[PDB]
Length: 246
Length: 246
Image (cartoon, rainbow over all chains, first blue to last red; front, side, top):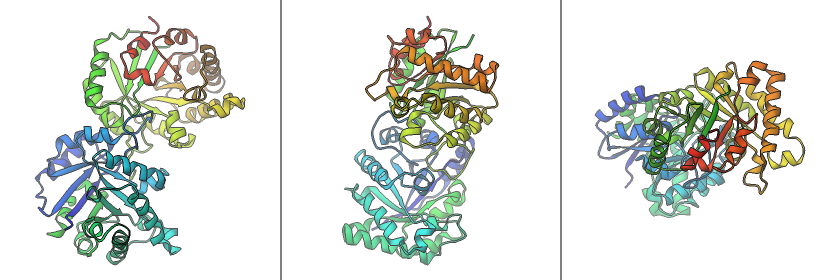
């Protein structure tokens, strides 16, 4: 019992005009009954996107901080995210980790607080190129996942996203088999360290390169439960990725 | 001749209902013609704040990034800020620098991009208790101001904010004479290093502790042209600070 999950990470892209247009497209898309869809707009447009999107698509913040209110110029809290109608937050995204230096310690604390506040969390992990080539893929993503698990009580509110950071802009790419390998090792970590129950019911989505051309082969991997989509999430092509199991 | 400037930095505080109430109070108060008022809401509420606020009050983003669009989950661009109807961005705020580790070099790149896109910039500088008790206040704030200056081609759209980070949350308080000392030295830096034109026209606002009772005296200091208000900007007290010259 794992419902197919497709998250669209718009990253720092779009304006009210172009996003309005894209939202119109998605509002007309037939989202399958077996599929849960979430879009993560730029923080300035969480409000806008929730107002314009049809309820069949949930809204995620791309990040948040770890307290409800405070002297943290530039941050938003899970309270504000809910106040705008979003029900998810993306935490630990590769860009937060490796461009903006967000530690594991910090990400775990955001997870605890987002969960305590009633949000769903799309919790991202994954290994860089140096790490993969040293043999420490397992170590790196287990450690990352351990830190997230320490701050989760209710796993029904969590989706794990594997980001093959080693394959992003590096000269390397991941095969569907390489994706499947990491996802079944992560499910083995959940079964081992949490419960078979949690393992069987927790979506592990793929956060590497995915397009309309590649989504069916990726979605048919037994341990790949969906996608955290980058570039293609800004295009009608997102609808094709949503239809991946159909 | 230099226009009195009050920036209200709401930091990570408020929800649509509470901010709606404060916005009501501000809309209702009369801003003196000789003063320029700007409010910086949490980033989730830039759009909301702009729509609720009277045109007499300007809206600022609390931070932004240094390209127009890109793969930066969690960030917003000056284009987005403008798209939301905001005309200012706060950059280099002590929380960005010291809680979130934003480098001077990063902050310079933001100033450059923000200015290029047509946004006003409230650029923040200041020394820690570390650096003041080491007698290197001048070195720190001038070096900070230099990096900013290197990424400004139009000073008409820049306000400098001195934040006495040494005297906020530390147990130490700053006197108006200590405020004036740094502000005078900053203006003299601009004279030496940019132009008399810039030195004489550039607002240097005070970002240390401002209350309804401390504001008149701070305001009368000749090189203190306004304030970047913390806690008091969330209260009707902001009105008193806006009226500090009256």
